[PDB]
Length: 53
Image 1 (tube, helix red, strand yellow):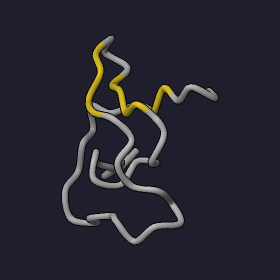
Image 2: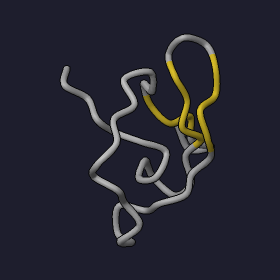
Image 3: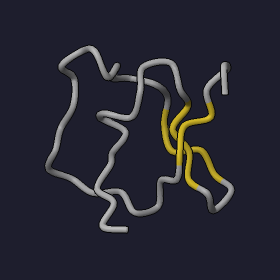
Image 4: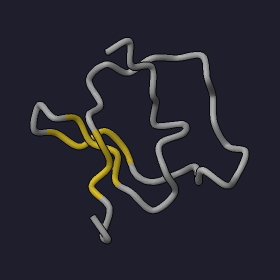
């Protein structure tokens, strides 16, 4: 709901993917690292298929 996450942020280590059944992009920004962009919105993304989860 009102999701506005993007491949910019996500989580460095998780493979950002969209529930549709297709990959979006790879882990590029850690929650701990300042490498986010709160501007865009990717309603297609669903989660990040990490090696850990």
